[PDB]
Length: 120
Image (cartoon, rainbow, N blue to C red):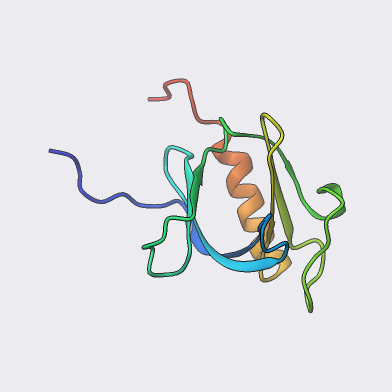
């Protein structure tokens, strides 16, 4: 039998610029131990927004002005911005509550990038 429950590296709330809403919407992100990243619609975790990998789907990580030619939401800086450059090209624009939150995530990702070859 499988474990049953899985613990996420870091779980928190983050905004995401949708292609249909063309705006920043508060979402729920959650990174897995295997690197895999999955976000939901709300704390309910019932409407699985989507699922994407980091060291597999994401190739580069930009933050702030470095990110695409996007723009931060109202009453929010730019350094708190977090983007994820996918392989093909897909680009996801995210935003943290404050630089602190952003930094944490960014670093967390840059770390999950070292996931693949057996470690032991």
